[PDB]
Image 1 (cartoon, rainbow, N blue to C red):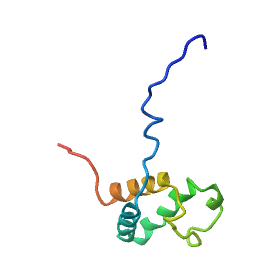
Image 2: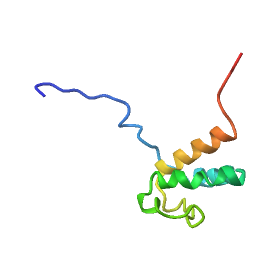
Image 3: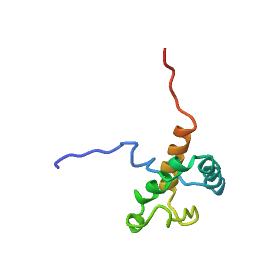
Image 4: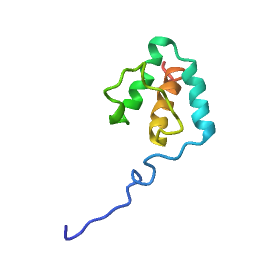
Length: 90
């Protein structure tokens, strides 16, 4: 309006790039998932690919080579929060 301002850290950290090693490491942890938990991985790509949101989970190949860095960061969270977690209960 008559005034405005910026400086929010959201825009500068939207999604960092993903190296070949990141994409490969993510594949290893994905390969450790049980069948009933692996079919949830494909749904993460549908959350980024509207072009894949009407395809079968068994007809969607995971091409780290065509997918966006942001997609991989979401997938990485799923595995790292499945195989591990951050809680210190009492």
